[PDB]
Image (spheres, helix red, strand yellow):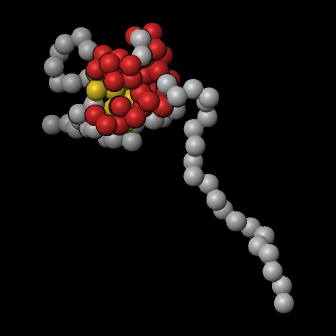
Amino acid sequence: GSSGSSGDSQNAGKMKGSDNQEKLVYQIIEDAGNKGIWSRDVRYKSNLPLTEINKILKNLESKKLIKAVKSVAASKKKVYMLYNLSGPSSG
């Protein structure tokens, strides 16, 4: 007659940082989907200043969470979409 368990795996997977700014933005980016989102469109959603959207949008690109993609249009812009996505294909 024995009891007790020695070895359990219980982890949800939280993100470091005592701030909820980089988490609110990243969520808005993934929402955009394959199409992606414009750095600006975020400023409004993330309700954060440009200086914040710039550092945030980038930071994520470092955590392999998102990436910078450019639409077929030859216009000076910058879209951000999940890093897992494959993006545009050749043809």
* The furthest residue to the right: 1
On the image, the x and y values in percent for residue 78 come to 30, 18
Q: Residue furthest front?
A: 47
Side of 18 where 72 appears, left or right: left
- x 74%, y 67%: residue: 7
Count of number-bearing discs: 0
Q: Quadrant of residue 35?
A: top left
Identify the residue at the far bottom of this view: 1
In the picture provided, is 21 more to the left or to the right than 69?
right
Residue sitting at x 39%, y 42%:
84
Q: Residue at x 28, y 26 (%)?
A: 37
State whether residue 82 is above or below residue 42: below
Residue for point 38% across, 19% down: 47
Which quadrant of the rendered structure holds the C terminus? top left
Q: Is 21 drawn above or below residue 32 in the view shown?
A: above
Asked whether the viewer can see residue 78, the reply is: no
Q: Judge whether 22 appears above or below 31 on screen.
A: above
Residue 3 is situated, as x and y percent measured from the top left of the image, at: 81, 80
- Which quarter of the rendered picture does the N terminus lie within? bottom right
Q: Position of residue 22 (x, y in %)?
A: 49, 26
Q: Position of residue 87 (x, y in %)?
A: 28, 36
Q: Is residue 65 visible?
A: yes
